[PDB]
Image 1 (cartoon, helix red, strand yellow):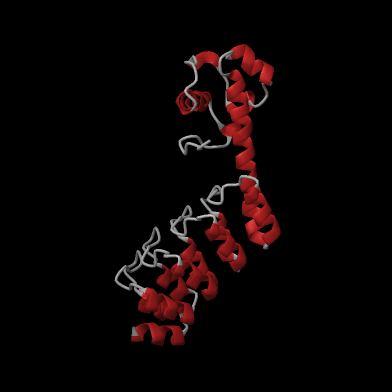
Image 2: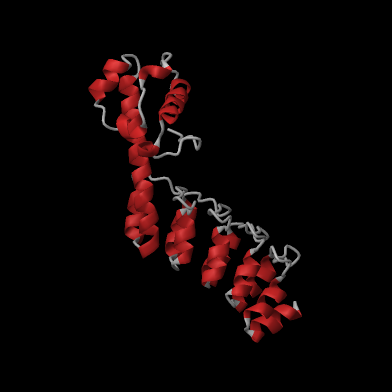
Length: 233
């Protein structure tokens, strides 16, 4: 059950055309008998109201499968909404139980916040560690294109940042405005983090959208110690 990103993955928000895309994917993902596109002429809000009997009456060959498939889509998407919230308040027990029941550890929210983005933003390093055990892509990006290394460097959790760089995080990954983690750390005034970024391979050449390096961002921030140290770089 590999959710196609083409589908908004929120059946309730599917359109009549989106329901046809889901049937088209399901016809090939499961090698089911050909399903007429007009079998379901409704939006996702309507599709969620039909019974399994209704699916059978509409598609005798695959209705069964389509309904059970649609039941798993609304189930895996629910576990992600619980894992994202659990990765926020530090419910490490709840974080490990949720992913043990089939929750996708790379499930992103509306802003594309992976559980790793939220865990690093709230100092939940343990959760980070257990998310990386499930193969969490540390190079993921949010709506703003900021990797978890960006949010970890901006929040000030250098212990997390070192764990991200240890698994190989893209240290030179620039933001949507070109703000590499060295820029978010220079804006937030993180000195050690920047020192950890420099040893792991921080790049000032990838300046911000305004053409400002870590020295310029720190000199524009107001903290001279972060400025002086960044200007020394």
